[PDB]
Image (cartoon, rainbow over all chains, first blue to last red; front, side, top):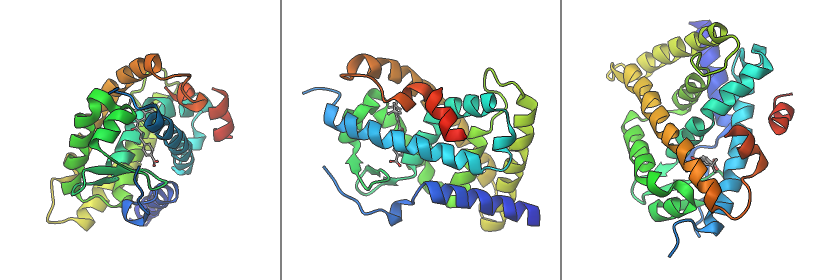
Length: 228
Length: 9
Ligand SMILES: CC(C)(C)c1cc(C(=O)/C=C/c2ccc(C(=O)O)cc2)cc(C(C)(C)C)c1
């Protein structure tokens, strides 16, 4: 378990450094389905989070030993997954809000009008589902890593290497959740099932991106185009 | 994927 403890700490640190927790942030607040002012802020903040997700990925042990082609394949396939999980860990239930990394705090109607559109209730439902899991940074980070380092994405050159980079992450999460939450013994398969729930939402989100492109005034920001 | 290469290297 010293190699496991090192892995958990590395991943916890990588998530923490690239994603402040809800309690650390100073919140601030601000006819047609897409409010272009909210869309502008939302797409800018998402761009910055994609950059932070890349910085998180590079700190995951082994990730940079994959070929560049596969690093890019993995990041593109997990982009919406990780963005959606991240914003869903910034949910305040008593105000029904989500808080972005600059502190911008939007309620459900505003999230709807920023771009989630018909996917708003689905995404807010998923955030509500995460709350009873009481995930800490190590757990959110490991779930993010497990979701990113997935050997079944299309067009991977070395999928077996990706699976073998993922298996230490799964074992770390299994061990960690046992030593943290012995009264919560089905918690590991419960959190892995959220990844599967998350893939379903992100598949619908990829559909929504096509409609958004037809609706926004100009172009998607360049990095978002690359990722999506 | 120009920006993404830069970010990774
Ligand atoms: C599902 C849907 C509507 C298609 C979609 C969802 C998201 C999303 O979930 C943004 C997550 C996020 C953003 C910022 C921060 C932060 O500021 O920390 C955290 C998490 C993003 C988009 C794009 C990339 C703008 C097209 C599209």
